[PDB]
Image (tube, rainbow, N blue to C red; front, side, top):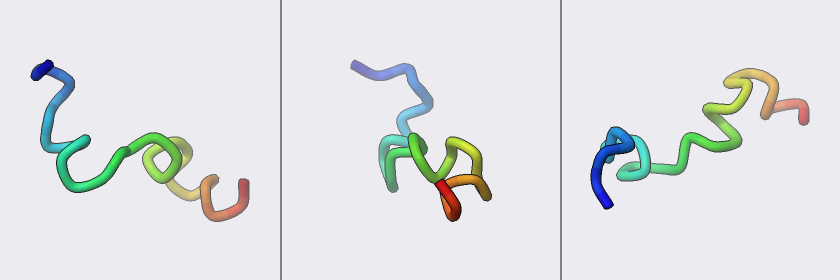
Length: 27
């Protein structure tokens, strides 16, 4: 597929890090 930004899933999955941004550092 190709629609979910693409650039995001490109470099790295913004699941955990992009989850809380700062929360992931203490999740």
